Amino acid sequence: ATLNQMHRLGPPKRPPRKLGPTEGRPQLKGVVLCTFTRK
Amino acid sequence: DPPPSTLLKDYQNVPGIEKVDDVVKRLLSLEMANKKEMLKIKQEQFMKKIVANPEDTRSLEARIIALSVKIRSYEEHLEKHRKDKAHKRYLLMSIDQRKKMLKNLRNTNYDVFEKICWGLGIEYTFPPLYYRRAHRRFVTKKALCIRVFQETQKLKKRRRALKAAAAAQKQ
Amino acid sequence: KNVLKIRRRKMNHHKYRKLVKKTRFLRRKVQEGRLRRKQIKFEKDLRRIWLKAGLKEAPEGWQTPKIYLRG
Amino acid sequence: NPWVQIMMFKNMTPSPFLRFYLDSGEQVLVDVETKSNKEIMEHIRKILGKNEETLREE
Amino acid sequence: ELMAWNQAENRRLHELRIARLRQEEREQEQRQALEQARKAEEVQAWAQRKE
Amino acid sequence: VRSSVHARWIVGKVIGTKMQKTAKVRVTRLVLDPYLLKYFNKRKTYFAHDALQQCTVGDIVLLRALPVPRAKHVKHELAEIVFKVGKVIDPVTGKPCAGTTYLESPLSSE
RNA sequence: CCCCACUAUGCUUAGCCCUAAACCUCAACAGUUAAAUCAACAAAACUGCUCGCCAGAACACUACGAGCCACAGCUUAAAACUCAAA
RNA sequence: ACCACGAUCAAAAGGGACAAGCAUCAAGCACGCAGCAAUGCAGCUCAAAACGCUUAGCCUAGCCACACCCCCACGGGAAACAGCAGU
Ligand SMILES: [K+]
Ligand SMILES: [K+]
Ligand SMILES: [Mg+2]
Ligand SMILES: [Mg+2]
Ligand SMILES: [Mg+2]
Ligand SMILES: [Mg+2]
Ligand SMILES: [Mg+2]
Ligand SMILES: [Mg+2]
Ligand SMILES: [Mg+2]
Ligand SMILES: [Mg+2]
Ligand SMILES: [Mg+2]
Ligand SMILES: [Mg+2]
Ligand SMILES: [Mg+2]
Ligand SMILES: [Mg+2]
Ligand SMILES: [Mg+2]
Ligand SMILES: [Mg+2]
Ligand SMILES: [Mg+2]
Ligand SMILES: [Mg+2]
Ligand SMILES: [Mg+2]
């Protein structure tokens, strides 16, 4: 892009990092509902 | 438009053109020529009427006059050819290029800019700041917001008299 | 080049057109309901204006038009 | 000079020039036609620039 | 003293401008003389052809 | 000489004259882009008191800060029309000009 | 797919619709052929300037919102889950 | 100490400056100006991002905000550790 275009866009807006199954936490407490096996 | 009897721009200054047979005058007049020959006469009239030097064709004044004659020709063409999209484009582009000339003439020579507008009958208009679709929801809300403003103004004046009247009674 | 990317889009578009054809009567009932809610949301937007300006009713002679109907 | 307004104008007059507006209300016209950019910088430094002594003290 | 020195530098540049403009008028007149001669021949030729 | 207005002297272009005795002036300043380290124009609007309604849209004007603002948005007054739109006078020669061309030669008055 | 018949339609007028592999998939303007010529292929390699656009795949010419003479439409256009590719 | 037409310190007020994401938030809906007043004019902001939504204490010798809630705290809900230790 041109300098005018880079100035007009500004710095690249980095998308906020997604949160995995733990929702950004190291561990979670849980209560077992059922047990089974997966292929 | 110039009269049909008007001589062509090329034959108007030849010596002895006023003493030739009437038939020769018809053959050298606008009546026997295409419309482009009538437009050259219109351009010449506007030049002498407006520009200080009618022989300078490269000045910003002459170009506005030359382009203004083309614009009137397109408007007359489109009056008879309303589905001619090619010439409708040429008209809109030519109007946009004359505004760009008038803008640059206004910025450099205002006294000449005024004579060009009077001479050609052009009403210079400043562009709108924002070009955005006035859709139904916008055109309805803007109308309501103007009505609401008008009503609030009336109520505020009826709150000036009642307060004024009560104040007088105390005296 | 191969047309493998076009082919993916070809099938996506084919299946979408067929889905719309299979459900065109349900989609028409949904569209009607959305336009009704859209009209109500518009009327509320205008009513908020005159109410926040101190008026108790709409400006004299004002009738909110139906700007989303086919008519 | 971050707090000094600098505004540029193209092709408005037949010759190039600088004009300074001072807080007192005085205006300083500097004709720069025929002068090199290095001469322009040296000219305005002399008439309106702080000397090296004033800067050392600061 | 610097404001007066700046006004004096401008007056000096003005005299150089006036001298430069005088040399440009003499050259403009020479060219403008030839173009009128040439333009007059083209008119007389064009006028004769039309006549 | 003291004033409560921040911008004491500013040059700008008149962009509006629809208010009574008030000219709307666009003032541009150079601002450094920290990443690109390039200067870009940043424009701001100022209302300026124009008692004689002599300002025309497009002319360059000099604004002077008032001692105290006279209105919510009017903090300056018209001090001088620097470049009248289409009627510029060359400051170097004092002669009228149309763009980069003189309308009256400097050699006329010697 | 092949043969026959025939309609909408291809035509005109008056209004809509606004979509194409609308691709010469190669933006406008100015300039260069020397240096390093240069991933491959294609239509040799580049400079200046400007606008537009792009940032893994798929989801997705999709959903929702909005606009529109469009009502099985068009334009604008995401996210979640999934993969280590594409 | 007092007076300091002073210095220091620092409110209120006036001017300027000052986070992030979303434009599928694109229009805001009174947001301006003049006048001693009466009143007059119809303007003001915005794709150079107004208005709106969402997120977040910040620019850390420290600063800002809050002090159970109703932004506030006459009043009301109600009966308060976001002081230390502690539950
Ligand atoms: K092609
Ligand atoms: K609180
Ligand atoms: Mg092949
Ligand atoms: Mg698919
Ligand atoms: Mg048929
Ligand atoms: Mg035919
Ligand atoms: Mg084609
Ligand atoms: Mg393309
Ligand atoms: Mg282009
Ligand atoms: Mg992708
Ligand atoms: Mg499509
Ligand atoms: Mg769609
Ligand atoms: Mg939809
Ligand atoms: Mg304060
Ligand atoms: Mg959406
Ligand atoms: Mg928080
Ligand atoms: Mg507590
Ligand atoms: Mg409280
Ligand atoms: Mg505690």
Image: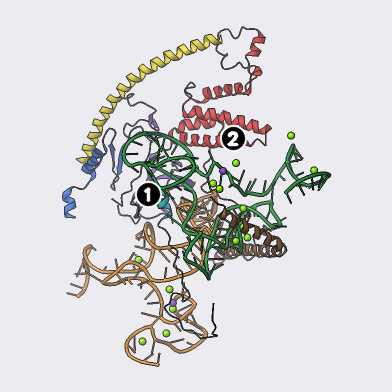
Chain colours: A cyan, B red, C brown, D blue, E yellow, F purple, G green, H orange
Q: Residues within 10 Å of mark 2 (few under 14, many from 20)?
A: many
Q: Residues within 10 Å of mark 1 (few under 14, many from 20)?
A: some
Q: Nearer the viewer, residue B65 or H23?
A: H23
In the rendered structure, find residue B50 and report the number of the disc placed on it.
none
Badge 1 residue CB within 8 Å of ligand 9: no
Residue F40 - label = 1
Callout 1 and callout 2 share a chain: no
**Is H6 placed above or below G3 here?**
below
Residue A14, percent from left and from top: 43, 62
Residue at (55%, 67%) from the top-left corner?
B170
Subunit ID for the residue under disc 1? F
Q: Position of residue C24 (x, y in %)?
A: 71, 62
Height in image: A2 above or below E39?
below
Q: What is the three-letter code of the residue carrying label 2? A: Leu
Left of B27 or right of it: where is A16? left
Q: Chain of mark 2?
A: B
Can you give x and y, in whole percent of width and height, for residue H40 in the image?
A: 54, 50
Using the image, determine if residue E36 lies above or below residue E3: above
Choose between A26 and H7: the one closer to the eye.
A26
Q: Is residue B3 left or right of residue A24?
A: right
How far is mark 1 from mark 2, CA to CA? 37 Å
Q: Give residue B91's mark.
A: 2
Question: Splitting the image into four quadrants, where does ligand 14 fall?
Answer: bottom left
Residue B147 can be seen in this image = no
Q: Is mark 2 within 8 Å of ligand 9?
A: no
Quarter holding the C terminus of chain F is top left
Q: Nearer the viewer, residue E8 or A33?
A: A33
Tag 1 secondary structure: strand
Viewer-proximal residue, H32 or D52?
D52
